[PDB]
Image (spheres, coloured by chain):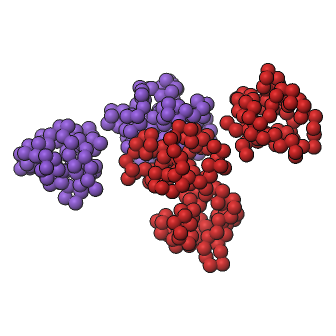
Chain colours: A red, B purple
Amino acid sequence: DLVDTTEMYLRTIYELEEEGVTPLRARIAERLEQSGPTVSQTVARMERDGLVVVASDRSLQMTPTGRTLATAVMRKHALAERLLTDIIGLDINKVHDEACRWEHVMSDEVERRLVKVLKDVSRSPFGNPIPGLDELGVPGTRVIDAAMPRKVRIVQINEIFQVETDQFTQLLDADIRVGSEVEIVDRHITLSHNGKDVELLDDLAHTIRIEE
Amino acid sequence: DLVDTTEMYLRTIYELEEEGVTPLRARIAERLEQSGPTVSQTVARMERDGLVVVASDRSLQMTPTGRTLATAVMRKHALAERLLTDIIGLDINKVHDEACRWEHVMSDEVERRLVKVLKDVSRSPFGNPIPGLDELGVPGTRVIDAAMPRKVRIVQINEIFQVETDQFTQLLDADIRVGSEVEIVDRHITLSHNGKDVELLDDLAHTIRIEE
Ligand SMILES: [Zn+2]
Ligand SMILES: [Zn+2]
């Protein structure tokens, strides 16, 4: 699958960098047991998506976008391994190869929950530290994207980017601020709290970021 | 992915049967949000693999092979859901749609381990009973296929299918029988126990079935 392939490629480039290897195409080809031509094809596709840039010396430099994605795949891999050894107790000799697949199906919601249920997510069972925890959020998701009712917590209001200041007090009345558990629902978006019902507007809807 | 697609189709046919619906192509198309033509294509491919037979009334009858596979996917789905609600504690409104992907990456080894770690695997969180536990083995794997050293347990010897009776006593000496924890290793296959080292031959290697 194209997506899964790219994710696998990005993770590979990440690993090599972490191991100290120069991410050269032939190295990635070897590690992924893919042929040079095949990887050139895939790498040539990643470039078109602004995911990687083949440096002047044929080394693959991950663009910020590609690295952000590569990181998320490492986090989903690592957490899968933590889950597999710690909870499931899968043979340590199977844990990694299995994780190589789980990283493509594990959602951020599951990841966040694993950060909860697991005793220690500092490193993977293989001693490689777990990246992207800050990015995972364990800032926040914008209400417009995160909002059926549900009770999240206000991570940020971002009143500073506001042009419309009418609902500032409407928020202050209901007592909605940073850390305020509130119940949202896209219908427009209305976030209730203190029995109060604050129906938001587009601008605030796009700037108020909440956590799960 | 072709395999994942077929697995998804087989599980769908299983579900419908379980719900009491007649597995008709248009029903599968609808449930999978696939088009009639696309499903006809995939179903036409499953036939070539002896996985399904389009009955005289256009209803898809799963061949024993297809059903055996369909079942394994239901087990891997169900156990994924049990894992997700019971251990991870994922929002029950996400559990199923997530599981629809996990069932394609979860291995029998993981399944067996989940049958261990989970409190109750009688039914899925959705009340549908978990099929294929007997087939999962929680008879056994043939030593030739299951055998680095590892200490499994003899599920069956199948001396009855033996033409060569030379190692019967060689086994009885080492005290290798049903329930005998032994250490195997393909080098040929040698299963040690009681300090004894019993190097097996092809015939017994293919008939002695052990569990993990
Ligand atoms: Zn790994
Ligand atoms: Zn389900």
User: Is A157 situated above or below B149?
Assistant: above
Q: Is residue B44 visible?
A: no
Which picture quadrant has residue B161?
Answer: top left
**Residue situated furthest top in the rendering:** A195
| Residue shown at 65% from the left, 60% from the top | A66
Relative to B174, is B5 on the left or the right?
Answer: right
Q: Position of residue A43 (x, y in %)?
A: 61, 67
Q: Is residue A26 visible?
A: yes
Viewer-side residue, B31 vs A174 = A174
Which picture quadrant has residue A110?
Answer: top right
Viewer-side residue, A29 vs B52 = A29
How many tags in the picture?
0
**Residue situated furthest bottom in the rendering:** A57
User: Is B4 situated above or below B136?
Assistant: below
Q: Position of residue B4 (x, y in %)?
A: 50, 46
| Picture quarter with the C terminus of chain A | top right
User: Is A159 situated above or below A171?
Assistant: below
| Residue shown at 53% from the left, 69% from the top | A20
| Residue shown at 85% from the left, 31% from the top | A171
Q: Position of residue B155 (x, y in %)?
A: 22, 39
| Picture quarter with the N terminus of chain A | bottom right
User: Is B45 situated above or below B121?
Assistant: below
Viewer-side residue, B71 vs B93 = B93
| Residue shown at 67% from the left, 69% from the top | A53
Q: Position of residue A31 (x, y in %)?
A: 48, 66
